[PDB]
Image (cartoon, grey):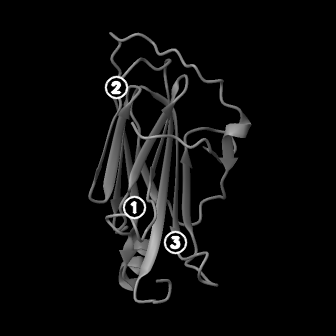
Amino acid sequence: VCDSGNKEYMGIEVYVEATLDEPLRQTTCESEIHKYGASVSNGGLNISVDLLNCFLNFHTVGVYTNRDTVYAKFASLDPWTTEPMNSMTHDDLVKLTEECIVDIYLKCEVDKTKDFMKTNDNRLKPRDFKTVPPSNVGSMIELQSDYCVNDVTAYVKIYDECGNIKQHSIPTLRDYFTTKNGQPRKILKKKIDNC
């Protein structure tokens, strides 16, 4: 399956962390996946991600809320057993590395008629996060925020699914965006479930 070499098999993880201007209120949770994109509605925020000239599909959408912050993860899963499969031709991979845009849009949908949520979880500690390497490429993330968001952070990693079979894998593409100033490059490590 891995060279082969007719096609490349890539995976993607997009992480979004958004802190609102007040504690989160009680909401329902909806998520959807469509062609080259996905979105999640939870905690007063709709987070949408669409991939432009990346030729990759998401397979799962996870979301976690803690106090004033929504954490989302959009990711691919096993590339050979999951549909739709994330294989691309070599020209598509060239197009990706030259033109891929991870377009992220936050839209506030806070309903102040609902009570604040009571978080049963501990405050998050440096132990709940992992550091990530710095941005690899040229501003892959294009992120639009909204008025209820005090800070937002996004991270994308696009990687070779054959990286543990091949001796020389396609180099991972990564980008990191934040409105935070003076904070480490960190992402929630706690794995988070679907709605």
Residue 97, visible in the rendered structure: no
Crowding at mark 3 (Cα within 10 Å: few <14, some 14-19, many 20+):
many
Residue type pointed to by label 1 = Ile
Mark closest to the chain's N terminus, 2 or 1: 2
Q: Disc number at residue 101?
A: 1
Q: Disc number at residue 28?
A: 2
Crowding at mark 2 (Cα within 10 Å: few <14, some 14-19, many 20+):
few
Q: Disc 2 versus disc 1: distance between alpha carbons?
A: 30 Å
Question: What residue is pinned by disc 3?
Answer: 161
Crowding at mark 1 (Cα within 10 Å: few <14, some 14-19, many 20+):
some
Residue 194 versus residue 7 in the image, above or below: above
- Mark 1, secondary structure of its residue: strand
Determine whether, in the image, residue 32 is placed left or right of residue 101: left
Residue type pointed to by label 3 = Glu
Mark closest to the chain's N terminus, 3 or 2: 2
Count the numbered circles shown: 3
